[PDB]
Amino acid sequence: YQELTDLKTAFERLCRHCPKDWTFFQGNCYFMSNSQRNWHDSVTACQEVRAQLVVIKTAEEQNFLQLQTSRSNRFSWMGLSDLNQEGTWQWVDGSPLSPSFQRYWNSGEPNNSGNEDCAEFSGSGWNDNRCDVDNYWICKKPAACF
Amino acid sequence: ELTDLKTAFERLCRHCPKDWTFFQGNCYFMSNSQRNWHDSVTACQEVRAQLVVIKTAEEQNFLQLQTSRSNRFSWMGLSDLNQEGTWQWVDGSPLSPSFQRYWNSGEPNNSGNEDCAEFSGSGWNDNRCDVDNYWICKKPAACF
Amino acid sequence: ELTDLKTAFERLCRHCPKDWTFFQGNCYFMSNSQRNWHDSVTACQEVRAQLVVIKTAEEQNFLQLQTSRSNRFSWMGLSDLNQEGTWQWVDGSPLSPSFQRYWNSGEPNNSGNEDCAEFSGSGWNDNRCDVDNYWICKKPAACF
Amino acid sequence: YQELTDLKTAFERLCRHCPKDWTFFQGNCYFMSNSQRNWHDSVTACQEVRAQLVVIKTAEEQNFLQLQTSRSNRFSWMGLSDLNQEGTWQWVDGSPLSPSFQRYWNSGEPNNSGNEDCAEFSGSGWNDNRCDVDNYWICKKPAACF
Ligand code: NA
Ligand code: NA
Ligand code: NA
Ligand code: NA
Ligand code: NA
Ligand code: NA
Ligand code: NA
Ligand code: NA
């Protein structure tokens, strides 16, 4: 198992093809929008380019993403929301926000009232915001070998 | 992770030359012209490949499916040139006992100077090595 | 056979673009011109690579040997742009505690707007991000 | 170990580069001469092209080689000899002829007398012959990745 991890990784890293203007990171391609849209229109905007409003699965991915948005100083949408409006945050892929990720919300975040059910990268952490607000968005999709 | 590694490998290394078909790690070339068995052998060597040597039942099945869309007869890397009823692949290996099942009904033959194998949609036939047939070349798929 | 597999892998996948140097699975590009830190970052992205992020002690050593033949100063994918004394690689990862040893004596600094790291023959120095330096790009070696 | 063997093999098979006119087989390149020379001159002739008078290491290699020489109906030298003239056959790489390979000699082969201390592929098996005789020869060298 010692080598398997290394080799497996070294191998998966060879398939790193991403579209033009997209950035590669650990097996996936990321797209930083050039315009702004509300949450819902961002969810569909990503599907149009065969991607998905970014669903964060590891702490390393979260670090990469936060660095990207802060580099351009833009507030960006992520595929996380609580549309049932009851403290249950879920990723657009259907998975639930794991306990170990609550650490990423900025102090005071999230909030039960105010009709703010969409997560965004805001400053050095996460903020919940009105889904109708206009923000940049980040798309994510598997990297290809060709 | 062992299996996941193969998936990565299987995913990355599946590059085949233009007009060759990929299948389980290899590239297969169905010719666009016919030649006798010996010239088919050199034809494959010229493209750094080998007149197809069948190693698995799946490959045999795949080649049958490919062949079925045209109903061709193709030379394969199998022969009994010394006429001993001793069939060998061009890589020197003997036709194992478990692969003898692939001969079509009535094949092979210990008579008629039919010392070469041809691949059809239902199995193998033995035939005169000088006959003109299409051929099938085989070589490993690449990674880039 | 595990190790023997790597040897095969290590042997086959060591292809690097023209003018890049291969080292333990990766390709390194020592620039032929200078730019500021941000333009160096985009310069690497333009060639499907990344301003070098150092992951092992061996790589650090290798880059020092490479650098020593010219005594250059090169931008590396490390910065503290928010000026927190919090250094991060361009892939988002924090400078681990065990890699802090590579800073040259007297580096880094919590003053002087020197928020970018430059690679020298003896270690790292922090410097104004607008200064013009050569740069080092990194990306995986290929198999063909 | 089950997969390791498959994968390892599938991988080694990707480095199959051989010179012009040389034939590839299981990780190595083989050259069938176009002229004839005695044994000793064949040993050096192969070194000139960065190879070695073929040293057979497996039964599968032996089958491949025997098929090659019989295809052209040529008697060919191999890197096997008993120059000490005392029933001790050794490969040019210094390794000894293993017990399980004695099966390849043609009936009656080898012989203690007659000054025949060099092995050749003769017919469907091996023959020992006078080293000064002219035969075709087969060179062998590792296959490259480039
Ligand atoms: Na909320
Ligand atoms: Na909020
Ligand atoms: Na026959
Ligand atoms: Na027949
Ligand atoms: Na500083
Ligand atoms: Na400094
Ligand atoms: Na003898
Ligand atoms: Na003899």
Image (spheres, coloured by chain):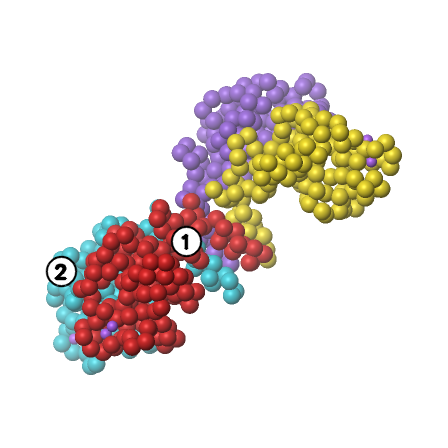
Chain colours: A cyan, B purple, C red, D yellow
Q: Which residue is mark 1?
A: C22
Task: Give the amino acid type for the residue marked by disc 1 in the picture.
Answer: Phe
Label 1 resides on the chain identified as: C
Residue B73 percent location from the top left of the image: 53, 25
Residue C143 percent location from the top left of the image: 43, 48
Question: B23 or C88: which is nearer to us?
Answer: C88
Label 2 resides on the chain identified as: A
Relative placement, left or right, of D120 versus C136 is right
Which mark lies nearer to you, 1 or 2?
Answer: 1
Task: Give the amino acid type for the residue marked by disc 2 in the picture.
Answer: Gln
| Residue at 50% across, 61% down | A4
Task: Tally the numbered discs.
Answer: 2
Residue A24 percent location from the top left of the image: 30, 57
Q: Please, is residue D78 above or below residue A120 in the view?
A: above
Which type of secondary structure does the marked residue at label 1 adopt? strand
Question: C143 or A140: which is nearer to us?
Answer: C143
* Residue C133 - label: none
Relative placement, left or right, of D106 versus C21 is right
| Residue at 43% across, 65% down | C58
Q: Which residue is mark 2?
A: A36
